[PDB]
Length: 306
Length: 306
Length: 6
Length: 6
Image 1 (cartoon, each protein chain N blue to C red):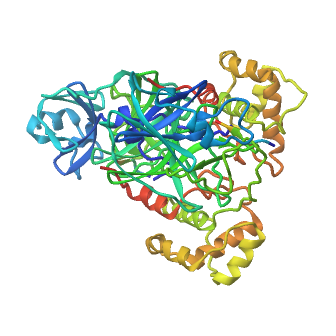
Image 2 (tube, rainbow over the protein chains, first blue to last red; image 1 turned 180 degrees about the vertical axis):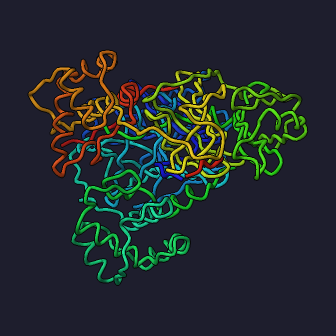
Image 3 (cartoon, helix red, strand yellow; image 1 turned 90 degrees about the vertical axis):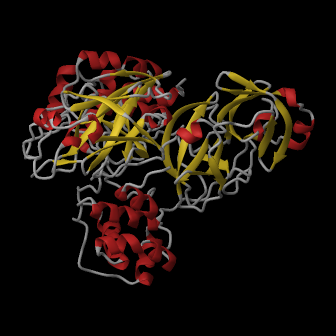
C-alpha cells in the first residue's frame, strides 16, 4: 500500500553524466559510447545570448575549447558537431558504463525521471511530466542544463529530455536528445510565449484508479456518463479532451478495479463541480495529473528493472 | 527555480541490493563488504507469524538455507547471526561496489530517500519522512522488505531505514540498520497501536521558506509572534512544538530570505486559522511537512554528491 | 487490524 | 519576461 511520486533508479544515468566547460560556461553532458551530448548554448558568451548565431559560434571553436570531465578523469575531445540545439562532442574513450539505451521523443502528458546535475555530478532525482504546453515543472538552477530526463524498461534507458533553460514563469524548457525543443521555444534569452497549460485528464483518471487500489473510495458514485458529456465538463474546467484511445489505455486499471472508465469519469465530473469538501485523495487536496496509467500499474504491481 | 520532492541519486545503493530467499519467503538484502543485512522475518513460516520465536527459528537454520542472489551471481553464505530484528549473513565475497557508508538512527521529522526493491532489483526511488509516530508513509508491496532508506553526504551513504512491514492503516514500519525498530513496533503479525500522528512544524516552516525563495509570497504578513504564543496555536492544530533549537536550525533560511523565524511563524498561524482561501503554495493546497531545513538548502543551492 | 510482513 | 539559460 501507499502511493508516492516515484522516480526510476538513477544509477544507469549517473554513470553517463560528465561536466562540459567552454569559455566561462559550465554545464552537464551525457556521455554515451564515445560521444558527449550537451546543450549548444555552452558555446555562447555573456553579451551574445539575445540572438546567438550558433553556426558562427561553433565555427570559431576548436576541440580544445571543450573541457570534458568524467569524475576525476578529463576526456580528450577529438571532434565536434551541432545537431539542432545540441552539440555532439566525440571523445577518444567510449564510456565503459554506457547502458543499453534509446532516444525517444515523448508526447505531452508522458512522465519521466529527471537526474538533476551540477558540474557533471548528480544532485537529486525527481519525477515530472511533459505539460500539454510543452514546459516541464522542474527544479533547476544555473548550471543544470544538460541534465536529462528518462524512463527505464527492463535494462534499457530511454532518454527523452535534456534540460536547457528556464522561462520567466519559473517552468522549464528543453529538447529531445536529438536537440529538437519541446514546444515552440528557441534557445534565445528573449520573451517567449508559453501556451496556456491544461490538466492531463487521462492522468487524473489514472491517479483516481491508484486511489481506489489503495482504498480511497469516497469519491466513487453509482453514475456513469457519456464520453461526449464528460468532455463538455472537461473543456469548462480547462482539462484536456478524453479520447477513446485514452479510454482503451485505462483498460487494465478499469479491469483490475471493476470500475468502468466512464464510471470513473462521473466521479471526476463531480469532483470538478463540487470540489473535495475538505477531504483528500492519496494525501492530496488537489487533483493530481503527473501519473500516467503506466506509472500507476508500475508502482501498484512492483515492476523492477534489470 | 522550482521545488520538487527530490530524492538522492540511488546508484550507490543499487549496487548493494541483493535477493535473499529462505524457504518460500523472498525479500531483499543489503550487501556491504562481506555481510548481507536483511529482515529476520525471512526465516518465518506461514503459520507461525503471530508470535515467532526467532531464536528457535534461527537455530533450526543452516547457511545453505539462505539463498543470496546478486544480479546474476549467487553468493555463498558462510555464516549467519541475528542482531535485534535483522539477520547478518556473512558471504564469501566482499561487495566490490560497497560505497563509503555509515549506519545512522534518525530522529522523527528527518527525511530520507527510499530505494524500493523486489527480488533484489530496484523498482523506484522516492522521498519520505520519519513521522512523529515513527511510521513512514511509504509505497511498499509484499516482497519489498529489506529495501533501505538513506541520505548521502558527498560520497558517504548514511543508511537509516530498512523496511519490514505494513500496518493496517497502510503506513509502514521498519528498523535502523542495527535492527532496532523505529517506534513501539515488533515483528509480529498482530494488532499494534500506532500513536496519533502530528505535523512536523519545523519542516512546514522550512517549506514556507522554500516557497519564498521560489517567489511565492502571498502568505507573508507584517506580524511577528512569540514562541510561546505560536506554540499555543501549534498545539491546537496538532502540530509539534517549535523549540529554540528548531529556530536556530532555521537560521540559514531566515538569513537568506530576510524573514525572521518568528515572523514566518505568524504566517503559519494565519494559514492554520484561516486556510489558503483557494490559493496554493509551491503547487500544494496543503501545508507540506516532509522537507527538512537541510532539504530546502540542498535543493535551492544545488549541492551535489561525490 | 493486523500487521502484515512484506 | 526573459528566458534564462541554465
